[PDB]
Amino acid sequence: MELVQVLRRGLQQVSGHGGLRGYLRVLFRANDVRVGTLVGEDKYGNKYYEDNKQFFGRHRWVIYTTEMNGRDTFWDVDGSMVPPEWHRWLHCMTDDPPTTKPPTARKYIWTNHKFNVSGTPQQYVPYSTTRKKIQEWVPPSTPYK
Amino acid sequence: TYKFVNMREPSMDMKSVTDRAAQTLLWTELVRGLGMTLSYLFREPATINYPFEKGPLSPRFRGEHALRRYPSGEERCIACKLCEAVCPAQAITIEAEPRADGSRRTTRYDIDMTKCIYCGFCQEACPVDAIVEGPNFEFSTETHEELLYNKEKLLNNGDKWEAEIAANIQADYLYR
Amino acid sequence: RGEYVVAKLDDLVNWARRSSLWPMTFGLACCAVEMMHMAAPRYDMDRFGVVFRASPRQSDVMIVAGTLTNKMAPALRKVYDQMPEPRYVVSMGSCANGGGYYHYSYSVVRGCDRIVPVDIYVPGCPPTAEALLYGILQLQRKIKREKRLRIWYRR
Amino acid sequence: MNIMLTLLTNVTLASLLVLIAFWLPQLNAYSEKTSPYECGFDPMGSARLPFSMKFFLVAITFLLFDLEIALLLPLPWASQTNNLKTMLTMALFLLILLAASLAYEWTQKGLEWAE
Amino acid sequence: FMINILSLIIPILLAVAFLTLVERKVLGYMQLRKGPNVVGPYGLLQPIADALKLVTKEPLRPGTSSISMFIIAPILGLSLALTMWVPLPMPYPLINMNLGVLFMLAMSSLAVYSILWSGWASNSKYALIGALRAVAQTISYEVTLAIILLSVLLMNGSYTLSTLITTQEHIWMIFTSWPLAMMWFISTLAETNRAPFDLTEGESELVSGFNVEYAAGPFAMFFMAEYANIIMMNAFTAILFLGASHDPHTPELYTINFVLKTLALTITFLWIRASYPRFRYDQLMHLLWKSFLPLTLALCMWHISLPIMTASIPPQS
Amino acid sequence: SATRVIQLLRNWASGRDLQAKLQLRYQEISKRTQPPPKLPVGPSHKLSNNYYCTR
Amino acid sequence: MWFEILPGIAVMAACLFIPGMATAHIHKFTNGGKEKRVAHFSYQWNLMERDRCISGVNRYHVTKGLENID
Amino acid sequence: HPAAHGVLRLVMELSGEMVRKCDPHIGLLHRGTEKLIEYKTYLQALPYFDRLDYVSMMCNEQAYSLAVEKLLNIQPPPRAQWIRVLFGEITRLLNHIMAVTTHALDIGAMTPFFWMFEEREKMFEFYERVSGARMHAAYIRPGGVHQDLPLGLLDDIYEFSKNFSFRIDELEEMLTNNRIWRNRTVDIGVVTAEDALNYGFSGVMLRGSGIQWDLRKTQPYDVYDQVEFDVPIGSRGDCYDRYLCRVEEMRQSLRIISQCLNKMPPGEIKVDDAKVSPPKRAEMKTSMESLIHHFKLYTEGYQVPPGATYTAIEAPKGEFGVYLVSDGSSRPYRCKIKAPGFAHLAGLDKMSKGHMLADVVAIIGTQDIVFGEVDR
Ligand code: SF4
Ligand code: SF4
Ligand code: SF4
């Protein structure tokens, strides 16, 4: 009886994951077919799930978005689309989603969380943050006195 | 007190000796490791799904540096240079200047990660909690010049990483 | 269109390259033991499709992990040059990135890049097993973003 | 000639694999890559010096024993003869003779690695 | 006719390729890991990914190597493994062969020669030593393998592989020569160069043994060769002891039974690979010449007089 | 957290009750939402009679 | 989750399938339904020549029964 | 080499495969650690010891911490010492996990390596919970630990220690009873009683040889006197004995965890003397004395009186110690690191005699050579 119980669990798995198209989407992109409660959904389209019944370290997980700042990422992904409010929840630094209690919003925090800009033209470059220290004596503008 | 580890003379009894002989001829203790290994195969693997899934962390984690700022907006750093004096690899270089107003912070605040050790000493050395060890372990890059930040990006890092540390020091301000 | 065809063969080449690249079993210092930490079942090196091979004639990407010293230098360059192309190098930890905690030491070369070309600089000291496992991922993305036979077609 | 056809095909199919694995996948050699491997460093310089065995004694006994087994390969056909009586004694006699030779070598040291 | 040859050769290569996936995946599941699953569904696309990347990798020709010797050995290794798949009594053998096992045994000894030659052809310590450990490994198993081979089929009637199906028939052959199968199985382990007896490779001891200067395509033919060798000789031990029933009107009924017999047995080859440390080739020739040889004589004497014992001499035809 | 039949298989192949406690972690761990602490003062935190010359 | 192992076997088992019945099917096809006749001794081999000769179409695997004689 | 256990140049002059000479050229990793020690202050010098050996994170600065404050005539608070010994025993588990499994890795079978590195990672999980990072905590400092453990950490320690005893049995089932492991291991590499301590060996090297010596019992330090445990003593001095003592030390380590867990006392976490330990953050932002001390402590460092000391603790390998020599200023003058591996690798020539090339692979793992520590 338990054998067909796990068979219907797979049949539930394909049904609950948006039918066949969604299941093939997560199987070939999300690399996993597990189904979890919709804990939250940020402004970037990143879909988040929580399954407290699973063993530790596999309770809270993320399905990444297909679009971020014109950096189409339906197939390729990396561990940096996660916004700062949710990045602590994903790493279970805490047992609260930002939806339950949002972080203290202030003026200067970024409105669009970015990722590693390495390789892209938006990459950082080191530069002097100090002014000139020894400025030279400017030659006189007048001709021979 | 001590416990002797390796000496147990085997009994030469007919039953005991045929046990060792059966163990020798018929691989029995040998298949014991083989047999248990089967039992461990059926265990579900303890593998996370990176980056879709990330390992557990703690609020007092050391990652990339991020210069924070006061709720008004003024950056906390006040150029006491204690972080520079403590930095075990001298990854910090500090220059200061009184500019015009209540904002003389740094002429230069360069943190050199490929020199830095990630000891976090700068974080608790700061009297105003300006420089902190951020919770982001994920700041890899392709060029060597990338792996050093200027003062500006420390501000941008503190600006971009702001909600996480604000809550992290909120939970950890009594421990330290 | 010729560019369409070359792009398709380009897609075939890097996908095999980034899926089946083989890191070197090379380890020097504190970073090496954390490198095998993620190879442990918690993070599963192999589930991303890579396996550890030993000799230079065997592997794809050099994974430099640990402090680089003057005495270690001749062998590292010899072993790196001994790897057939294509070959990539990632630099574990602050020490191998450049200098590190012993940047000012007499017996430490300030940078593995001073000896061998580097693709990715994975920071942290030691880098957490999560961070470098992304470093492999970034190299998969970097391997994806090439036009080797495509630049040849327009060459 | 059926065995010839599969033998020819087999060695052919192997040769294509080495053929396109030597020309198609680029070529770039600059000496130190071409150099021998000594776990990172430069070899003492040889790979041709006498690598003297320490088990030379057992090697020749293998030749005697691998030879003598060829004497008892005809056993399946040797069973189906009208004279299994002397067949049993002679075939047994060979196995004791190998057993005695193994026993002889065993007792006078032999199989254990010569040092 | 050649259509039969390709259908005998081509599926083996894909089967060998998918052996690399299970090698890296059931081991991982047997090791708390999840195995390769990032490339396609559950990693089934990984064996393909290995194939092209190895082929497109740069071939390497060491300066001190003998060029002709460096190339002939990989050809010999892969060709023998592939041609090893023609004579098995898989329901309708490609070539009926009176001396089925002798054909099996002869080129199995020639297979190690490709293993043998590559060591010095690469011209270094780490391959010369691995090549010479191949000498001692085949010093041990060859002196006894023929004895086990003779003993098991002495009740069959002849050396023909096809008669194995007739001989077994009602009951599994292992039920009659179980201590021989104990002898035979792990001696095949000692020739395929698997974990307990892989001194020719020797991962930890000498980097890679007879592979150190090998790269790209030459390995691809070498990797497939030894993976083809283990599956084929496992299929050999499948028919040697676990031969199933064969209905002439429905030959496919034999294939489904035979395939699982050589497949579950293969899982064992991956099973020992995880659980057991490495034999030192000192005890390898020591063990196979101290206990293995004196024992295998005794049952060989047992298995010859015993057809005479009960008037159970098998017919040759 | 698997089927009972395989649980018997794992418990019999290894010959020990693994199901009582496993290598992987579950909800028996402490939650990571601890209440604020009230860390104690030290022995020398006495308001008087704490001259440095005596310690 | 060892049921993820089975897909590896599933294709592999099917991969081992092809040379099995094919070696039977091509034998069935090339010999006209009846299976491949084997000749381990002179009697069997001397037969195939006689069957090849008697058929009159130079095929050993086509057989003429009692209707051939009158 | 993967069997090289990192980096070293081990030249064998061997005939056939019997090693005649096995000169272990060391220093391929050399960092002038003691030289940079000279220019950094004691607080800046703490992370150095955390990076000597990559197997025992805070076992090392425990020796370094014991070097400083014991020279300083200062003692840590009783609660701090219990944290030190508790994590030192957890740290003792850390080395022994791959002191045996990576041994088995070079030996052959790789599955034991992946059995317990999962549990080794859990000890990393509490490591990161109570400290700043996973590996290099910089936690154990002179005068006491850096900060208090997070709430709920001890309960996780209890569960893990409860589950761990069921895992050494997993390794021991895999290896100890195994004949294949035994044949490659028993009587392969032996030391007599006299040459054991004549060669400067320590820890498991002596204990396997039957030498009745252990630093925890003979010369107790911190709160190790109150804890009760057993030390496994070998009978043959071969590789099998050392591996068996290493396994039994892990079991005895778990017993120490149980006693440490149930005997955690209340109180502070660092010496109340603010001149040696930084004051609390709340006091540093409010009181003058805390702020001015914090400023000068985090810009000069505590002045250590002139003198010399050779505090040595029971490292998981041997008797890892430091010959701290202070000139009286705020920075140390000379600090020479005693490495148990240094003596063990020195004796490697004596161990390998008549054994083959696979056996020397077994020996260099039975001493658990780590080349940031053996080399310094
Ligand atoms: S952790 Fe902070 S104080 Fe320490 S080296 Fe890095 S930046 Fe400097
Ligand atoms: S970051 Fe903090 S410690 Fe460093 S100079 Fe600024 S205020 Fe001082
Ligand atoms: S960067 Fe840190 S962990 Fe890595 S080798 Fe250097 S000191 Fe060790």
Image: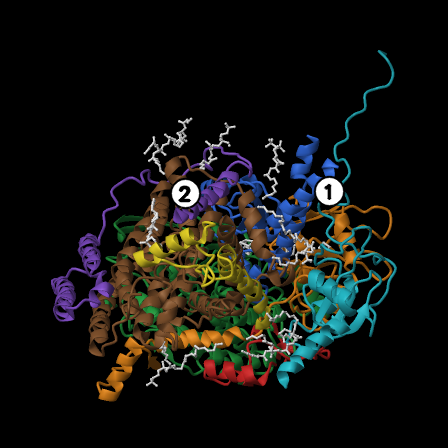
Chain colours: A cyan, B orange, C blue, D purple, E brown, F red, G yellow, H green
The quarter of the displayed image where residue H3 is located = bottom left
Q: Residue at x 54, y 73 (%)?
A: H76
Q: Give the quarter of the figure containing the C terminus of chain A.
A: top right
Residue in front for this viewpoint, B141 or A37: A37
Looking at the rendered image, the disc whose residue lies closer to the viewer, 1 or 2, is: 2
Residue type (three-letter) at the residue carrying disc 1: Val
For badge 2, the amino acid type reads Tyr
Q: Is mark 1 within 8 Å of ligand 1?
A: no
Q: Residue D37 bears which disc, if any?
A: 2
Q: Is residue B99 left or right of residue H57?
A: right
For disc 2, the neighbor class at 10 Å (few under 14, some 14 to 19, many from 20) is many
Where's residue B30, x and y in %? 36, 74
Residue at x 36%, y 51% (from the top left corner): E111
Dividing the picture into quadrants, the one containing residue E95 is bottom left
Query: Number of marks in the image?
Result: 2
Q: Chain of mark 1?
A: A
Residue D54: x percent and y percent?
Answer: 22, 53
Task: Give coordinates of residue G53: x percent, y percent.
Answer: 41, 51
Please tell me whether mark 1 sits on a helix, a strand or a loop: loop
Q: Which mark is residue A125?
A: 1
Q: Is residue G30 visible?
A: yes
- Residue H323 visible in the current orientation: no
Residue H280 found in image quarter = bottom right
Q: For this view, does A82 lie left or right of residue H7?
A: right
Check the image and report above or below for H162 versus D106: below
> How far is disc 1 from disc 2 in space, using C-alphas?
40 Å
What secondary structure is found at the residue carrying circle 2?
Answer: loop
In screen coordinates, is E68 left or right of F38?
left
Which of the image's four quarters has the N terminus of chain A?
bottom right
Is disc 1 surrounded by few (<14), some (14 to 19) or many (20+) residues within 10 Å?
Answer: few
Residues tagged by mark 1 and mark 2 found on one chain of the structure:
no
